[PDB]
Length: 120
Ligand SMILES: [Ca+2]
Ligand SMILES: [Ca+2]
Ligand SMILES: [Ca+2]
Ligand SMILES: [Ca+2]
Ligand SMILES: [Cl-]
Ligand SMILES: [Cl-]
Ligand code: NA
Ligand code: NA
Image (cartoon, rainbow, N blue to C red):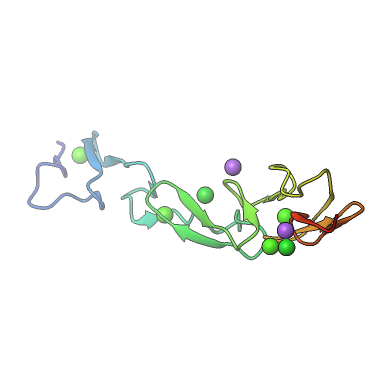
């Protein structure tokens, strides 16, 4: 004789998991982001510290999201944004990459941060 645990008053599977009856026991089909025999674990997607460079990790349902510290980008904030990519230095100035910052080394005779000032 078998008792259907799923048909009973309450659902033994936590977090809206699907209850599937078996002979002798029961099993839980968990939703994305939940684990355990009764879906009682909210999987920590931030447990392995996936966010890099002092970024903040958000433990979400079935996913993680990284809030990047200024100057960094990407899903894991792994990319140090190249501020020289957009070519900010006018009149062909040398660009030096920093954090959320660029450094223009202006040609002769220009100045100073974007090399826009013509000294004539
Ligand atoms: Ca059963
Ligand atoms: Ca989670
Ligand atoms: Ca940078
Ligand atoms: Ca600047
Ligand atoms: Cl992210
Ligand atoms: Cl300037
Ligand atoms: Na981008
Ligand atoms: Na300038």
